[PDB]
Image (cartoon, rainbow, N blue to C red):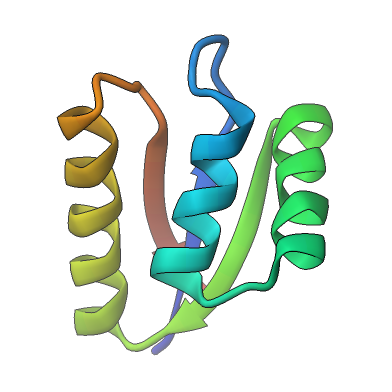
Length: 81
């Protein structure tokens, strides 16, 4: 089993922060990060990758922790692929 890791839309997290997260935690360049951000905003969410269970778990925890440390509500989730 592999797991999707997803970012979900919200009304407060700034664009530049979503881009930052996509680069830091998912290794996307600016253009692709920005595309994924567009999907977050207009599809309501974007799948950012597929990973092993333990890697997905760790990524979800770390992205959410990073977001809250900067007082943003950005929500990262996992689900079975």
